[PDB]
Length: 222
RNA sequence: CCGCGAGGGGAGCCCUAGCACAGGUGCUGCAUGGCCGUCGUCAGCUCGUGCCGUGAGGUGUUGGGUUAAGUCCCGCAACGAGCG
Image (tube, rainbow, N blue to C red; front, side, top):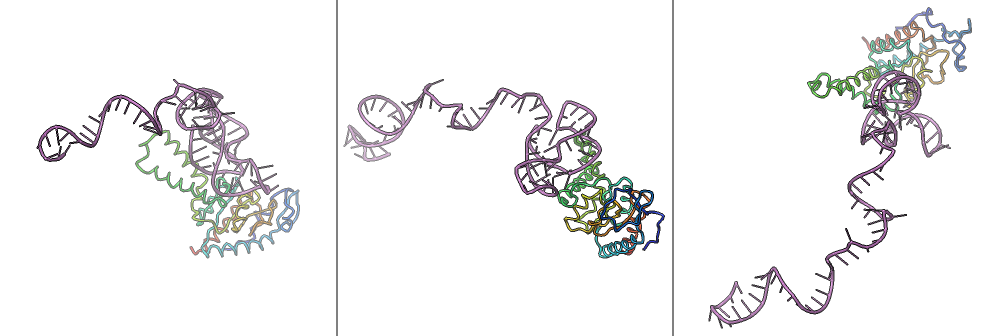
């Protein structure tokens, strides 16, 4: 799919906290706010979506990550709706530089899941019980999505890049493509495929991902 | 053990003379083992990988909350692990 001129959504976001480099991406100031040139955003999209389509049909993986409070619930949704891995709760230092060391935690989840189904439950101390029950809890928070990662992702779809600059930093050093729903406050110089756009607005993130995930699907053929 | 005997060599055991050596609570705990006192039953000491730093190093083990406790919670470039 391709989507309209639904301007009733990401006209602009940040005050004057911007990033000079972002200049190319803005229309003007109105009431002390930078307003993003959409005619342009469209030119970006037409590229960014071109990319993902390539990925989808090529059968790759894209990790969705956005730790912002607003996008929180929407990240979960969209990745879920897609055949994708996501990072909802919090981003852990190294889900890429230190993947192998992290993947070991996954296994922990894998291995605890088991015991909370086997006979060897209550049969053994109760102090440990809770001491384990807790471990699951926490794991099934952070790694809830991270679980689907068999190996390193072919791309990272980031929501607020300047907030996740870590996750970007990582990707940037492993040569993994970076997509982002960036705005005024970001430094485009590091997003492989940007999408100039308001983001704190649930209506923004909600649209950008929808059409993005929709695209992903129609690309695979379902 | 030997040819019947007489007696002859031999094992163990004994003394004598010489020898190898036995013995020494004789020095050195700054030459040592072991075992113990002690800070201290105090809550701490550290490692792998990741990341920071030219480096020595750092982060993690920190902060805010909590505990008898590095006991647990929230948070955080870290995620774990070991001795405790």
